[PDB]
Structures are given as C-alpha cells and as structure tokens.
Amino acid sequence: PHARRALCLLLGPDFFTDVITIETADHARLQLQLAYNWHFELKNRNDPAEAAKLFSVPDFVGDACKAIASRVRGAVASVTFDDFHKNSARIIRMAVFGFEM
Amino acid sequence: PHARRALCLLLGPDFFTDVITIETADHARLQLQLAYNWHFELKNRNDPAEAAKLFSVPDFVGDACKAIASRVRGAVASVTFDDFHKNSARIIRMAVFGFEMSLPKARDQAVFPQNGLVVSSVDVQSVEPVDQRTRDALQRSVQ
Amino acid sequence: SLPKARDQAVFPQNGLVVSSVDVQSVEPVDQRTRDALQRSVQLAIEITTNSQEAAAKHEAQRLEQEARGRLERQKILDQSEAEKARKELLELE
Amino acid sequence: LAIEITTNSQEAAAKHEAQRLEQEARGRLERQKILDQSEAEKARKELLELE
Image 1: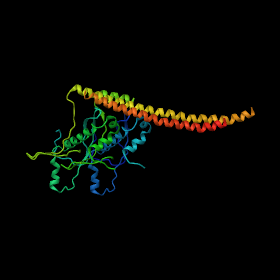
Image 2: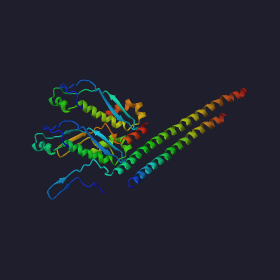
Image 3: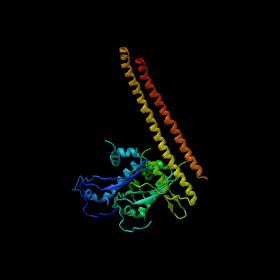
Image 4: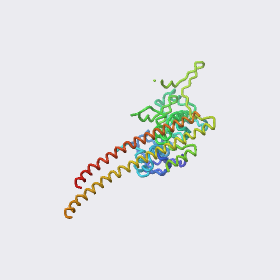
C-alpha cells in the first residue's frame, strides 16, 4: 500500500512489477505475476488543469494494480482451470480491458 | 469506528482499504476485501452551503463502508455459493449500486446525497472462505 | 411499487428520521445451531462437485459416442474399399 | 430440526436437478446415437451393394 515516496512522478513508458493471487471456477487456487506496460497520455502539457489532474490519484500504481487485480480475479473465477491454464494469455488479457476487435 | 482524526478532509480520487465478512445462502461463511474507488462530486465549489454540506457526515468513510457492507451482505446471503464463487465479480458489483444498463449489469456509480460522496469502482481480489474445513472440501473439487 | 416498503422512518415526537438501516452480521447465538449449519454448506459444496463431475462424465460419455460414431463410418468406408478390390480379385480368382 | 429439513430440501432439490440433468444429457446423446447409426446405414447400404 505504501513503500516508495518520491516526489518525481514517473510518467514515461514503464511497467509494474506486480503479482496477484486468484481462484478459478474449479476451486484451483493459483497466483501469477503481471507486467502492465503503462504510460501517461497528456494531450495538452501546456494546460494547467489537465497537467495538474495527473496528481488526482494519490496511489496511481496502487490504483491501477488494484483495479486490474479485480478485473482478472472476477473473470477468472467464472472460468474452468483446464481451459484457463491452456488459454490463459487470451482471457486474462481481454478481461482487464476493451470489449472486442 | 474511529482511528484517523485529521482535519484535512481528503476529497480527491482514492480508495478505502476495507474487508467485510459475509454469509451466503448455502451457509458458507466467507470474508472478502473491497476497494471502493471514490471521490467527492461538487458541482459548485463557490457555493457555501453545498461546500459546507461536505462535512454533514461525521464518518464519511465509515458511512460508505457500512452502507455498502449491508448492500453486499444482504444480496449475497440470498444467493448460492457455487454460483457466487463463479460469478462473484458480477453480482457483488451490481448489488451495491445501480439498477440495470443494457436483466443487465447495473451501473458504475453510487452517489451519497447526504454529503456528495460518490463511489465509482468497487474492485475485489480475495473471496476466501472463513471456515477451514470448507476450504479443505473445496480442495477436493479442484483436485 | 406486494413491494419493497420505503427508505424513511419519521419520529413525530421530536423530528428524528431514520433513512437507511444497514446490516452486516446475522449470526446464530447458539453454537450447536451454527455447527449444524456448517454441514449444510459442507453439503452444499459436495453436490456441486458431484454435479461438476457428473456433467464432466456426461461430456466424456458423449465424446465416447461421437468418437466411435465417426470411427464406425471410417470402418464401413474401409470395408467398402475392400469390396471394390475384393470383387476385382474374385474375378481374377 | 427446522435447519436439517431445509438442508434435506436443499440436497433433494439439488438431486432433482442432477437427476434431471442426467435424463436430458443422455436424451440428446440418444439422438446423436440414432443419428450416427443412420449415417452408418447410408454407407453400409452402399457397401452392401459393392459386397
């Protein structure tokens, strides 16, 4: 919840070294590591309000890691293990974002 | 009920580090952690009454955590465990707020008209059974 | 809307009004009660695992039929190709 | 006693569902069998002509 405190808010391309514990529909408890290649998308750096809106969230890494952890854990628990283990990379990716392509 | 006392009422986007214990229709006692991505929605900061209405509730985090805890615990207790465990993320989310959207997924916003607090997302991570013998019997199901 | 009653109780003696009445812990007082209820949940899990393995059996039982069903058509097909050559052989024989 | 009969009504209703699922599962399986046996006759008659 709270370990690094640095005043320089890193906003460039980077990833979160995160791991999450989840349970599946077959009651097979399994935990996994995620990457989360992220960045901040400012369409107007000159704008004061939009640039100051960066610091609206006090734990942006914790907010993103928490939000996504719920999106995976919820979807994976309504899916069988043998199907997950096999086709994991697909359903885990589309569960955290988007609708179709 | 009462641990932080700070005079600076945080109103920006944040979450509540909360956990709740609930029972389901199959009498399977299981407790889980919630997130509650919240913020305050002031449509007029210049207004004195509406801005002073922020401090109407004396325990805004306790009020929201209590209110939602009842909305989950009530709905989950009238639902079977095997259905819950599988489709938890759906019913727990729509139980705390909204009515439908497209019957359908309820919405992604609960407003508290007492003070102006509004909860946007309610992420969940650990739906663990409280009883040990329960989780042992569930280990056979996966095995 | 019989229906859900409302979300407000007014006390006309003093003006107090109760809006929400959230609840969290409906726990049985007696211990032996909650122990008997622990069987209900421990029973409510085993029949779902039985319905799981039964539905899993039904699938594998279905897969058995449809697997050998197409195999049976392959057999009749292979036996047919034999007759196309056996009749030709029978003429030479 | 008022708890054990509800768990009996629970497992009885749970049995009724699995007992229903048994019938409807093998019911569609039976139609698959007759269908697969029909495709065999479509080829067996053709084979019987060559035989």
